[PDB]
Image (cartoon, rainbow, N blue to C red):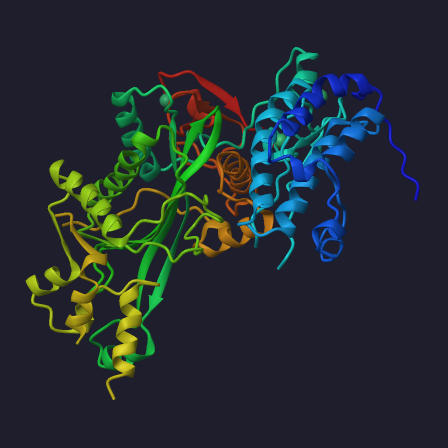
Length: 547
Ligand SMILES: [Zn+2]
Ligand SMILES: [Zn+2]
Ligand SMILES: [Zn+2]
Ligand SMILES: [Zn+2]
């Protein structure tokens, strides 16, 4: 029953201060006519004919009761007023049908309150005056989390202030109490910029930023593109196709590929926001037919908060066109896209999309890729592109073993169904002609210069979806996506599986204490090499060995 605490520099509010600040908002509700009228007195179920009411609404609340408390002085902190206005709204929204008068009255009162209470609560030193709950995820909704300033005691929305103890382990200090300090907040070192770079990531981001510079739009921020996971996998031929082609030795039992997960982030309001993500499968020059030198885009997802909107599509295209150009240069021959719009509520990569992010009609989605590919053809990056059906006929395919066979793809499961219902494949291909693109990119072996990044969280799409569902990292709004990115990036920086050995770029020996180049992407010399091999750039001394 007993809980002790200390809080000397606490913000404490005197009644009159609140009223002078708060009640101009409670009055803006009373001024709503006729909408405020059912809310000026406690709901009387015996006047209205609804004995129902007190069984459904457990804590009645209304304007008059709130006006009393604001005059009684019963509100010590400003959140208690705000909690009571939202309690009023939540009662009405609950009991009444979304079509009734009162429910629509309520949404008008609430829209007014949102506009009034935000600037006021911010003048009192808070983030906003909203009540937030996370999307459904029964009956219950989970409440957003709060942080208290270790100085003020002012309760804040953790998502509003974007505070996380891992980044700032000495705790949350509100922006004003930091002004009573001179020193600003410490830098967030768990940023997108600071994710390990790759030639693949760099080529894509170098291409997006070069485009954004020519655009010179003032709302735009820097784009960071990062490969965050890669590994070597195999796809096993399924049992039907196995007995039909593997036992004879016409198809290999499994096909090797390298999978990669990559994300793009944009600077928006000075923080990292993840707006684009993609998993790919890459079948090299030692992969047997039919997968030799082929890349396939398994899953592609996006969140529409990129700034500005009028550049969103062009930047998605720049990443995709950049991916084709990159693997074309390394030696891949064909690319494949499965252009399928999500089945409402299926999140491809990011948990919980914005309610008003458009799910495109399949004709629009395919036109979208067509425009991207047409753009690539124009720049002479693509040699040509056709749908799977027109392409199969043009190559005179007659056997199922000539269809590329990719992990998790549509066609391996169509082939299993065909074999199981045998006792028309060209018909199924024409039927879904529009959904499957075949991209012609064009030799010595393919050698990927990037190393593998072990990151279980991004080894395929399920691990990150699950973690975001459990942690309520939604991408449903700009403010929630900012928070989700923040924590996503903390997970990549600190919970990955790679540990780093350092070698001298000259004699290749393992180093502890070392000279690290300030200019080159990643260049080191042991003490001995620093003492013999000249390097023209300034170098700094890093590490500290125990011998
Ligand atoms: Zn807030
Ligand atoms: Zn504070
Ligand atoms: Zn050396
Ligand atoms: Zn250098």
